[PDB]
Amino acid sequence: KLANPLYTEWILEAIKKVKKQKQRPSEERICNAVSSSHGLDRKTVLEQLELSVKDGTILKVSNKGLNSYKDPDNPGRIA
DNA sequence: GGAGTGCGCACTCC
DNA sequence: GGAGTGCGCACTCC
Ligand SMILES: [Mg+2]
């Protein structure tokens, strides 16, 4: 398990927040949300997002270079 | 003034 | 047909 589970949880909470705002849960929106909720800097959030995707605890969907991240508990439309 | 948020609506996709 | 996605702004906050 590469990501810190505490940070994975905060990122999953960020994904839920951004989804509820009806925006794509992108890297940038996730970083801003986790900065607001806990003061973690952009570099650390980006690292932990990538590690969580490698762990399988966060899902990554890519469309022509643009990424959307999903909670395994609420994966929405996935193929 | 600019960051942040809410959501109606056009578009996607099954 | 319609549920899901997120774009585009009206709106709110400091
Ligand atoms: Mg969970």
Image (cartoon, coloured by chain):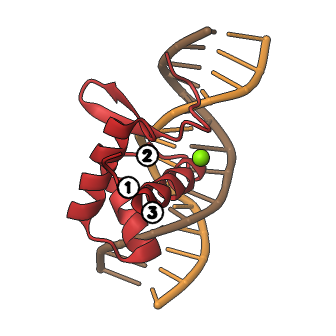
Chain colours: A red, B brown, C orange
Return the residue at label 3.
A6
Chain of the residue where label 2 is placed in the rendered structure: A
Q: In this view, does A70 lie to the left or right of A3?
A: right
Q: Disc 2 marks which amino acid?
A: Pro
- Asked whether the beta carbons under mark 2 and mark 1 sit within 8 Å of each other, the answer is yes
- Asked whether the beta carbons under mark 2 and mark 3 sit within 8 Å of each other, the answer is no
Circle 3 SS class: helix
Cα–Cα span, label 1 and label 3:
19 Å
Q: In this view, does A22 lie to the left or right of A26?
A: right
Closer to us: C6 or B2: C6
Q: In this view, does A74 lie to the left or right of B12?
A: right
| Residue beneath the point at 26% across and 70% down | A41
10 Å neighbourhood of mark 1: few (<14), some, or many (≥20)? Answer: some
Q: Disc 3 marks which amino acid?
A: Leu
Percent x, y of residue A21:
56, 53
Return the residue at label 2.
A25
Circle 2 SS class: loop
